[PDB]
Every structure is written in structure tokens, then in C-alpha cells.
Length: 309
Image 1 (tube, rainbow, N blue to C red):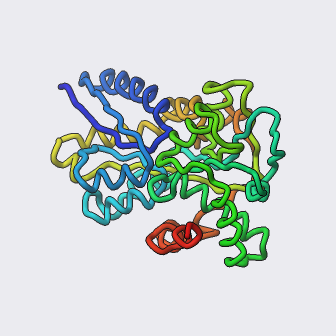
Image 2 (cartoon, rainbow, N blue to C red):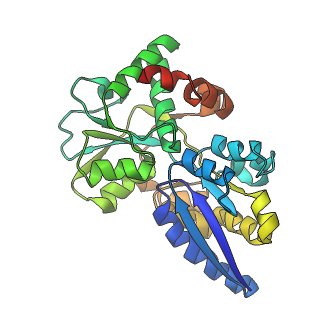
Image 3 (cartoon, rainbow, N blue to C red):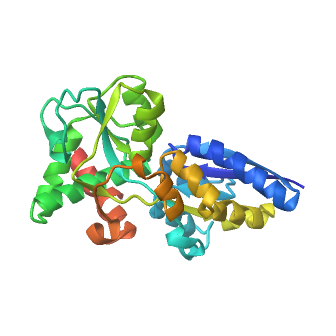
């Protein structure tokens, strides 16, 4: 049979899925004789979730954080208990947040505190549409808390000061990366680690340098089958198989090659030297999980709205 799947994903996974889709299709045909074609859609995680809620017939969603999937489940398109369906809370790989600066680090950026200095132009996406934007915001807030004796007012002041320095707020993380690298705007990009490594290895070798902060957040992008769509399109078996294969040694290696941190020990050892080492905190330990964080910081009249005013 000929099967057509649609994967609605976050912004920077464009390269990953171009490569992964060809490997999964070859694998599925080998095992079943069927021909599967996967179409891709990319954009800020928030915006993408909304589009699915409003009619995009995605078989699978591969978003930047668990909240965005939950938002679709809350609207009834996905089973409420979707996170337990795949291992590691449906997160086949992890990432983190680092800084990308221009060659020679002319503004002498060393840690989070340097981003609030006068005259520094910061590039970070919009928390209202981007998943990476929200990870970035939590990383900076977590740092502030940890450097201010857990004083939330001081952390809010810190983040206010960081946002005052933001020159362009793109809607998706790949837009942020293009603004910095391609358009040459900004002194520092608060980037997904995969974007920083892609920029220094491909999008512009010898023009950029990564700065690893003292601590950052552990980012866990999450995947899910869209129950209501697969039940209509008769694609549950292949959609489920597509997400499970991300955990295969082949899927993990494709992730690693594209600068995402793999879970598979065999793959991590093989691509070890690529990932900076740094202290990571999680969303559960510092913010009480996604439900609480989203509420507190990104819902209407949250912390973000507050510091923007």
C-alpha cells in the first residue's frame, strides 16, 4: 500500500526529519513491503500545537515540550494519558540551552549575567509561539533564582533586564537562528544546543563560537501519535512505528549526527566529544513541572506579560 503521514514538528528539526524520514521509509518497506511517505511541517511549537487543535491532520506531533502536546490532548485530539505511551516520558532525545556569539566574543560573554549588561544585543524567540523561547526563559529564571537566594522578585528583575536587551523576537527558533547567523543581527543568540552546533559546523564555520553557561535547563522535546487523526486515516500502526523507531540505535544515531543528545549509551559514546559538559537543572525540580510553569510564566498576565509591560 502507499501511506501518507504528516509530522507537525517544532522549528529546528528540519534537517533531522529530512534524514530520519528517508531512513524510516526504507526500514518500513523492508519490513512490510508498504511505501510510506512522510510530509513535514515546522514552526514555533506553540503555533504548531494550535494549528493541530484547529484542523491540521497531523498523524504525529514532535513538539518542543510536553505542555504543547497536553494542550492538544485537553482539546480532545489526543488521549489524556499519552505521555506514558513511549519511553522516557515520550522524549527520545534531550537538548539544552547555550549561547552563540560572534568569533572572538567581542562583548566578552561568559555566563547568563553578561546578557543583561548595557549595550548587549540579545536574540531569543517569542515565548508566545516558540517552545525553545520558553525553555530559554526558564533557563534564565532558574539561573537568577540560583544566584539570588531563591528570591523570585530578583529573578523577575533579572529576566526583565534580559528582555530589555532583546533586539528581535522571532516566532520560531529557526527564525531566531537566521536573524543572528544569516541577517547578522545581535551579539548573542540564546540557542537550542542543536542550533548552536549546526551553526558552528555548517551554517557558518569560523564565524561563530559557543559559550557554555555555568548551568542551564535540561530540555525534553516530546512526541505523540494524534489519536483522532490516526483513527480517521487508518495510520495508527505506522504512526506508532515511526515514533518508536526514534528510540532504535539507527534513530538515535541520526539524532546524534544532527546534534541532539541521544539516550542510547552506544550512540552517546560514539558522539561524546560533540556535546559540552555543564550543570543541568530540570523543569520539575525548579518550576514544579510544565503545568505550573506555563501558568505562572506564559499564560495571559503571567510573568512574561508582566516584564514586557
